View 1 (cartoon, rainbow, N blue to C red):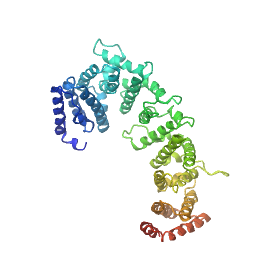
View 2: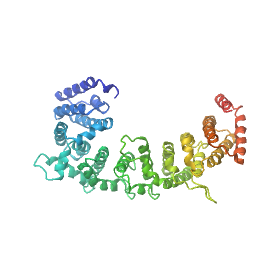
View 3: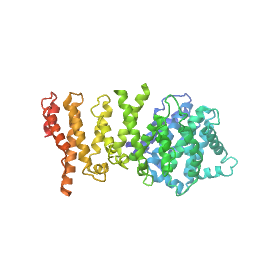
View 4: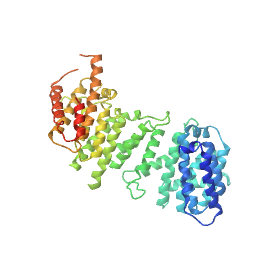
Length: 489
């Protein structure tokens, strides 16, 4: 991809040669690996037009195997342009461009002629929509009266999609394909600013309602193949739908609801994870809109954690929680404010909400049943100690709950190290060193701003226990452990 930025022609020339060889030759070959290089080469709007024209000329004469490879490769190329050049995609609909429309239309017919059987239709339908998207006005005419031949073949295909998309037809394969194709149409729409308010927005609204019932029906789990559900597919739909209508999502509650199966929860958390990490377009909605569900998110953590620990000490049901729990932990690592909003505050007879969160993360570090999770729990607790994230624990008094809870964590973890030897002992110590660094800074600024800084009994009763664990590590056999322990003084 990096190489293709400058010397496009050199790479592009190689592809053109292979097409000609296959075009003239009549002995079908399976060395299409050269053809499949389009999926990685950087493409721009002007360059993309070249690809369509060249393949169009030679498409009809290619062999069956070659035709499939170019179709798949061309599909993945389209997204590269949109992602790498978001602005150019918007301008396509902002101002008409006949040249872009012309090449797509010719290719559309060639692909349509190629696919006759139901099995063929499944492979090519995802591509056809992208081509249809490229030509804006052909969509408008399809909605209105249909031209004799110009907009006749297109209109027949578009309505054929809905039948399989709605399950009317007795064809599972087309039903599966219709989902894939429809999602991509929704995904592409997200980039459209909607200021044009073209038919694209209207077209999606027609199919969105039907799509959700197929993918978000708790009674019937949509099972594309061997896996119980196509987890990846649902994620794209939910993320896209959110961006279209972020104000009041209607399925967030359905997925977030406890009665729904775990897989619905798994899709929900991952979706919230992408929003935080991958937001290219500014005018998209942000995670802030979801803060209102923070209270409900925490409740899920408690149930998942409680059942996860019990299993370690059904077969796949237990394993499901561990995977779900791992995803939940990573979510807090991405953004801690999501779960810390609307603090419960310490009850007269019950503990608050910020405390129960820390205790759950702490009880995973010395586990050794789930080493992969434990590694993350260390990182998670190390992010809630940054000066920025200390405040959110209890905004009423940020310099009283910190020492009450943070110190109590040290007392629990330190007592574990001294109690007996563990396999990961040499690793917990390196993490414990940075915790001390990250609570000195909070005291330094706290003392500067206002000395007033408190020293409750736990601060003393836990300062002792810290020392009792740094002497006992000096005789530890591991050379790294003793060196690290000495530096902790």
